[PDB]
Amino acid sequence: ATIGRISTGSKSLDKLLGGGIETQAITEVFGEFGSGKTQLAHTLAVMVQLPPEEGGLNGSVMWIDTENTFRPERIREIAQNRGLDPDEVLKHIAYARAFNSNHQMLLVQQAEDMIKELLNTDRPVKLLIVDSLTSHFRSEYIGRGALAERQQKLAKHLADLHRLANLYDIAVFVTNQVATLRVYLRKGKGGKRIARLIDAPHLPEGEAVFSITEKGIED
Ligand SMILES: Nc1cc2ccccc2cc1C(=O)O
Image (tube, rainbow, N blue to C red):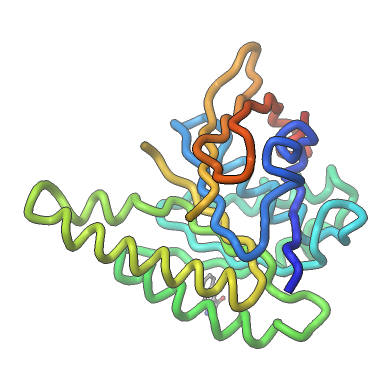
């Protein structure tokens, strides 16, 4: 289908990204604790539920959590501050906690069941979040003798995510620490945050400054 764009809530960040995050693509956001990557994930889980006129895609969300960072109270707060019903917004976020890298991989495969069920409805899955992509892979595969299998397993996981994104017109959004759009977050001045786009093949490298508010991400 046509490439849909989900607003991040920030006009500055959306301009940097070419209008927002894309369906049929993996957007990978990097940053240290406090850089705003989890705030962006929570904001996008709300924004995607809005109609296109308001920066969303009238969509449902699937969220894979590798380390206990999903906060339903933060969704409710962002939803209510954006004029949405907080309970309805939460009902349209399917949640899974992944306990290890094998289970994380299995969940991406299992997500296809619900994606297929909602595909021709009024609320198709339009956003699949994996927070935080490599935490289990880094913990489970230590050192020299483990790199080949860690890379093999991560490549398969990413291929599985790209397949769902392309086949079902979903924006895949992943968070991490240091063929996919890579955005680097950092602390800016006066409690603001900065996003830097690096090595995008068809978007200029640039920076966007944004704030974290009761609405989640905004300028
Ligand atoms: N069966 C499921 C699989 C998932 C896979 C990825 C993200 C969320 C998911 C939620 C469920 C659920 O039963 O609520």
